[PDB]
Image (cartoon, rainbow, N blue to C red):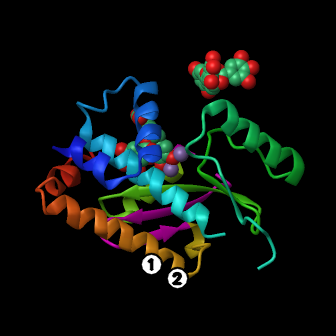
Amino acid sequence: AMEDFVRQCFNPMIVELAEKAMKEYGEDPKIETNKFAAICTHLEVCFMYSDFGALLKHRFEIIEGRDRIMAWTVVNSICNTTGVEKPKFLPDLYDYKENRFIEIGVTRREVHIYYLEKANKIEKTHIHIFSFTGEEMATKADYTLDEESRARIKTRLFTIRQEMASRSLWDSFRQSER
Ligand SMILES: O=C(O[C@@H]1Cc2c(O)cc(O)cc2O[C@@H]1c1cc(O)c(O)c(O)c1)c1cc(O)c(O)c(O)c1
Ligand SMILES: O=C(O[C@@H]1Cc2c(O)cc(O)cc2O[C@@H]1c1cc(O)c(O)c(O)c1)c1cc(O)c(O)c(O)c1
Ligand SMILES: [Mn+2]
Ligand SMILES: [Mn+2]
């Protein structure tokens, strides 16, 4: 059962944020278990990406995984102090070094298409897509992180993928992203 996997594979904080998020949108984590696990994955990658952070003490501000009220407080704080334009939707991070917001995507399809669907849904937000195929794609080929950091994100995705596969959950998870 994909539900049981999610609760074994991901830390309880991540799992809880995934539930809250699904319920906010009216979805039952016990029925839409593939989506449940997708959300956990997007969450964990955002935090991983966050935790990689010479000059600045914390290079990234984390925005995903917060209640919307705090998310916008943090986003408006950053905007009102750095002067950067205010997004129309909440992104996932802010980069203090490059002074821009980042929208992380995670797909189990080919990056190039998911990238495009993301970009259309936003415009000054830097997009960075990962996939379970091991690929990635970022606006203007600027991957923000070093290669050490990205490889760790990619390992984690592949680690999730093998643990799914071993329990035959993978192929469903792969097909459900429609
Ligand atoms: O975080 C994911 O969902 C968030 C919660 C959510 C939901 O509950 C229902 C719904 O209609 C939309 C929805 O948008 C949220 C979301 C936030 C993101 O930052 C994001 O990149 C995204 O694809 C989406 C997510 C990410 C994914 O990458 C993904 O494949 C997935 O199935 C889900
Ligand atoms: O609801 C506030 O905090 C949390 C965030 C939040 C949200 O994002 C969307 C939503 O549908 C409800 C919602 O409730 C949350 C909340 C958290 C609590 O710990 C709590 O006791 C509560 O009554 C509720 C809140 C309300 C306020 O009126 C307020 O001034 C404030 O600073 C914060
Ligand atoms: Mn987000
Ligand atoms: Mn995202």
- Which residue corresponds to mark 2? 147
Q: Mark 2: give few (<14), some (14-19) or many (20+) Cα within 10 Å.
A: few
Task: Please say whether residue 61 is visible from this viewpoint.
Answer: yes
Q: Mark 1: give few (<14), some (14-19) or many (20+) Cα within 10 Å.
A: few
Q: Residue at x 45, y 75 (%)?
A: 152
How many circles with numbers are drawn on the protein? 2
Quarter of image, res 153: bottom left
Mark 2 element type:
helix
Residue 75: x and y in percent read 73, 43
Asked if the magenta segment contains residue 134, the reply would be: yes
112 to the left or right of 126: left
- Which residue corresponds to mark 1? 151
- What stretch of residues is rendered in magenta? 121-138
56 to the left or right of 67: right
Task: Please say whether residue 135 is visible from this viewpoint.
Answer: no
Residue 43: x and y in percent read 47, 50
Q: Residue at x 89, y 49 (%)?
A: 81
61 to the left or right of 164: right
Between 159 and 81, which is closer to the camera in this rendering?
A: 159
| Three-letter amino acid code of the residue under disc 2 | Glu
Residue 17: x and y in percent read 47, 39
Separation of marks 1 and 2 at Cα, in angstroms: 6 Å
- Name the image quarter holding the N terminus: top left
**Which residue reaches farthest bottom?**
147
| Three-letter amino acid code of the residue under disc 1 | Ala
Tell which quarter ligand 1 is in: top left
